[PDB]
Image (cartoon, coloured by chain):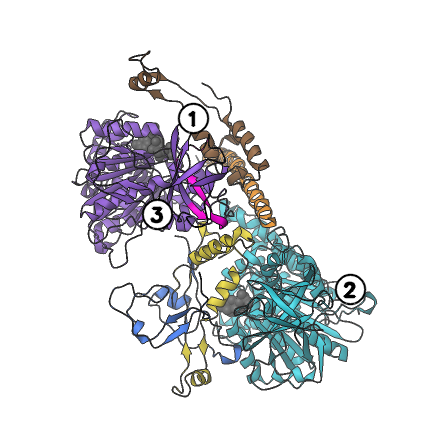
Chain colours: A yellow, B brown, C blue, D orange, E purple, F cyan
Amino acid sequence: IIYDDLSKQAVAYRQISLLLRRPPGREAFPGDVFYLHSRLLERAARVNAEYVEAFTKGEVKGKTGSLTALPIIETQAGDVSAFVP
Amino acid sequence: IIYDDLSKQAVAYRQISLLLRRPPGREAFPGDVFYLHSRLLERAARVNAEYVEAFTKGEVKGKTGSLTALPIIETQAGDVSAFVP
Amino acid sequence: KVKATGRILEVPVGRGLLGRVVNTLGAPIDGKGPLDHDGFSAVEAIAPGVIERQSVDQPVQTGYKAVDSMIPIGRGQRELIIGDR
Amino acid sequence: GVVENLASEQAARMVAMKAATDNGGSLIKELQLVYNKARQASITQELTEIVSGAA
Amino acid sequence: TGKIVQVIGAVVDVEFPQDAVPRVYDALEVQNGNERLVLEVQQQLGGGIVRTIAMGSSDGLRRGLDVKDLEHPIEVPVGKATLGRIMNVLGEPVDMKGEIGEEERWAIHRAAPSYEELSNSQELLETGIKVIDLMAPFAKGGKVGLFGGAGVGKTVNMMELIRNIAIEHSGYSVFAGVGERTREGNDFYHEMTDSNVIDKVSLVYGQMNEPPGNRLRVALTGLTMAEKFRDEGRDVLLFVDNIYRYTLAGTEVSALLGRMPSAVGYQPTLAEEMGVLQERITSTKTGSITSVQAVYVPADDLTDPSPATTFAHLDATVVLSRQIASLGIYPAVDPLDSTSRQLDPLVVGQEHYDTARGVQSILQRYQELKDIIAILGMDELSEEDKLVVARARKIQRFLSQPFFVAEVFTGSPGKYVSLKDTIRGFKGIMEGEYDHLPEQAFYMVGSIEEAVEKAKKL
Amino acid sequence: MATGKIVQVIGAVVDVEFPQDAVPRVYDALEVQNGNERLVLEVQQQLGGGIVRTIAMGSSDGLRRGLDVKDLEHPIEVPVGKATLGRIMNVLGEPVDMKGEIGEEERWAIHRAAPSYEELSNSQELLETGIKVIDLMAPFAKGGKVGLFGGAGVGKTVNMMELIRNIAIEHSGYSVFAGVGERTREGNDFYHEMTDSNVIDKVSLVYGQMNEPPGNRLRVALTGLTMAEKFRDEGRDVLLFVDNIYRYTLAGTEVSALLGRMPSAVGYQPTLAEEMGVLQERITSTKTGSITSVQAVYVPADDLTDPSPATTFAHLDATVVLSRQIASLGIYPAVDPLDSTSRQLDPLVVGQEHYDTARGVQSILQRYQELKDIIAILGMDELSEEDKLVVARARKIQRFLSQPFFVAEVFTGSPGKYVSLKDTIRGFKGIMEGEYDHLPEQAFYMVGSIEEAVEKAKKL
Ligand SMILES: Nc1ncnc2c1ncn2[C@@H]1O[C@H](COP(=O)(O)OP(=O)(O)OP(=O)(O)O)[C@@H](O)[C@H]1O
Ligand SMILES: Nc1ncnc2c1ncn2[C@@H]1O[C@H](COP(=O)(O)OP(=O)(O)O)[C@@H](O)[C@H]1O
Ligand SMILES: [Mg+2]
Ligand SMILES: [Mg+2]
């Protein structure tokens, strides 16, 4: 899976958060921007064959499933110190 | 007309805008500092004879008025790239 | 009036999505007809736990010499592509 | 001809090092202006964000 | 039926009865003294109050005045009627001629075309400008952006593109002045009407002297006319004078509308406001809008949130810069940030692609050498490095060109250069055919030949 | 019986109203049925009349206003003892390894006060490690705190896996691993590694990964301490490894504003220094028993000046500053010998030859640093001969700090090397005294003892 611009998601969540009047953080991003991207990315994983067999109720045996992710970020003038990067 | 400093009018407007708790922008100037100067300076113009005839109700005819305006700005250590300049 | 349907956001999921351009809610926008989904799934779920993982030892090939020699990606990895515009 | 070329060499080196000294001062006076403008912006980005957060 | 309850600068709050509160973008009318003022609804607050933006001067309004609820958006004339004429944000005529004889009026808040409706064309378009169609060539139907600060030449370049690309375009065109100098509008109007091409160019002007309501909705009444012409099957050219000012009017208003500030002080809806504007300006399968936009960057800051969220919306970005201008090299196009989607050998050819990459490779290496030269001077360089410094300086001089629209400021006659001439010139310099000519020979000349002649007279 | 009702649910923060008698006290636990899911809430503030504001120890999704809440009249209490050895648990001390119940004898509250000033015990019992640079520049005693500072990707985890290998296997005492905010894959890879090596029977593991709601990441560090403190009070010598102290502070930052707190200097919470203090002053070696601890410290943006790394520098006995420059140059481990130090680096407590070698090494490398930009602009030919000498010896010293690790073998395809402390001193003294001046720089790179430097020099 390729996430085209986790930066523009962070920007959309910031807009939603501020319109809802939640308290702003650094650069005005809400604090749960780390929680947003971390809960999203830790979903990409490889799972052992016991998990696959348990999930598919026995149909598939002997196979490990996997999801790979390639998030993309834009930095401004190469600044890595900004919040979302 | 010679506005002797538009960079101390911009400061005297930033003070009023900050005493009214309006959210500041770049260099803490208010968001409408551009409107502040654009409305003032765009009043310096050359107007065609039809406008002078319409405004004076025909008492002045065939003459074109004008208002030249040379504002002064002061810049810190001679950079033009500041916000107000 | 607003009613409260007590159900979280779910999305069409299946094999019949391969080749389809879809909006966030699962509506096709390519105009190639409706989907053929294998049921729905929930948008917001939790990830597999520590015991349910397996380590990464299988490659996913980029095809780019620089990436695949110096910065290899495996099936379950979470590689970030970062840079300017 | 060799001894005279070595005297010429020392004169050319002193002129080059004098130029390199003035150009180094010229860079110092301009990098300092970049640094001062940056510290001022950093000081105003914060404070703006602490007052906005204090709400 | 409703009454004004607050007047906070440009925004106006109106209280309505509980059962007839206006919809989220309807228009209202007030008599502000002897004048009628239109208001546009932005928010429905509770208890039947709406926040509105005044489309005109807000002075003189008194609390307790009575507003009148029109039951439609701002609707503007469109089509063949709006074709030789100057119009207001409300779509009123602004020239002293009579009324606009329209058959139809469209609301200005519309939706962007669907995904299946779009069309992608690689049909390349040719400009007389050497650097623009060398480095970042743009095709018909794609958006072009001219970035840069104050005084770097955005408008003079756009007047050059209006002059040249109108040579190979037959159809109608729309010009939208969004918050720029009125004088530049009046000069453009007289220049168009003295060349008798005013019968095709349609003008909208909400300029920088106008209140923030007028500078917020003027870009949208520009598009609504361009979209009318696109849906008649025509290929339309759309020129926007400044599309920073549309976001600046939103920044000025959005504090008083109650939204909390975002980064710097921009409105939190910056990326949506720009996305709602710049996604209805596209070539569908039933028309095509070729558009040029001038994007003021604030404070020369390319990392600012307003330019940085516009670089993703454009097909060909041309970044003007102040240093290159101070050297006198007009057009002051920085060739290490300007790029395009159409600079690919599969669409543009290999000889062009190779020339443009060769130029970038040389000028980058020159940038790396400039910091060494600054402390030590040129004498400590390698002899190959001195060769690239000489060719890179000649290339920078050769990027300049004398525009016909700049003949007043300078005196030099203008020049139009073809693509084959410019790739021949840069290919010749890159392989050092012209290594024997002085640098000042390349400054402000058209084709390479001309430079040789200049060199003869030094 | 249930006694409170939910009145707000804004993100991760939940407010509960109770009768104005018997309002829950601070740091208490509460329980609510989030559908079928039993959800724990921790009380953070008593605000207003009868209301308490709380953090969810689980997902906040699925909660309605008006749900009944039951107040447990105790803090979060966790299993402690031998029954915790070999088991993975979450912040609540519930098994996540699917091996069944923990079977604990005793349970302890995770919020407790630190040892009194008269309880603290002095030690200088220097540990030896295989790592050359650390044992030269930052040796540390049993019972001390060690911090590994670095930005992203500089070698914090690989170093901590090496130190776990070298120290813990010789250690006969029980160990605790606290995976605060760890990546789930790295937690599984560690668990399997210990399970294969058969050292899992003397380690207790507490894991709070990145995906978990902020309360878990906030409180999981305290469950690690509560287990280690049980072993210390039994009188054991304990090894405590904490995967990031930084994501405890960050888990505090995320929820701080929703708790109503005014923001501080870099957006951090106003209580950053107290939150760090209250945790880090429990990690001490008392008269009854000793905790020895190794902590990794993330450095946001690679600036050592950011409040979070800046405060934690003042709590640690040894500080091994890793640097991204040295990693980018490809020298591993990327320890900066000029910034890293220990309070055990004293001539009195180390051997005086060790101290003299360390002072020499640091003096030489500092003298190289100032020459670097001079050579870069004006060129090596405009050094003098004694500087050309010290720039060479500096490069030889800066290669001999590198080392292959057994746990960093998978990355590089080479065997792993363990160097004894004495051999390290003997080598660096020999290099500075110039006994190996004639050998090339690569004869010192990625080698073990200096006898191996002469063997590889012969092969070269
Ligand atoms: N060939 C040229 N191209 C551009 N500008 C030129 C050229 N020759 C001279 N100039 C000078 O550059 C000035 C500034 O150009 P222009 O008016 O386009 O600025 P701008 O880009 O419109 O910026 P803004 O509208 O924000 O002031 C011109 O008025 C002219 O005086
Ligand atoms: N001693 C080493 N030998 C070889 N590779 C290393 C070494 N130290 C770090 N690396 C490389 O750098 C990576 C990042 O460091 P790691 O400890 O995994 O994450 P972090 O440093 O952020 O905790 C390692 O995964 C490995 O790729
Ligand atoms: Mg302009
Ligand atoms: Mg790590």
Q: Is residue A26 visible?
A: yes
Look at 58% across and 52% down and name the residue there.
F369
- Left or right, F202 with respect to E146, comes to right
Q: Identify residue type, mark 3.
A: Leu
Look at 53% across and 38% down and name the residue there.
B27
Look at 37% across and 22% down and name the residue there.
B45
Determine whether the beta carbon of the residue marked 3 sits less than 8 angstroms from the nearest atom of ligand 3: no
Q: Residues within 10 Å of mark 1 (few under 14, many from 20)?
A: some
Determine whether the beta carbon of the residue marked 1 sits less than 8 angstroms from the nearest atom of ligand 1: no
**Residue identified by numbered label 1:** B41
Spot occupied by residue B81 in the image (x, y as percentages of width and height): 46, 35
Spot occupied by residue E51 in the image (x, y as percentages of width and height): 46, 44
Q: Identify residue type, mark 2.
A: Leu
Which is more toward the observer, F323 or E97?
E97
Give the magenta range: E42-59
**Residue identified by numbered label 2:** F348
Element under disc 1: helix
Q: Check if residue E51 falls in the magenta segment.
A: yes
Spot occupied by residue F382 in the image (x, y as percentages of width and height): 52, 45
Q: Are marks 1 and 3 on the same chain?
A: no
Q: Residues within 10 Å of mark 3 (few under 14, many from 20)?
A: some
Question: How far, Cα to Cα, is label 2 from label 1?
Answer: 77 Å
Element under disc 3: helix
Which is more toward the observer, F300 or E159?
E159
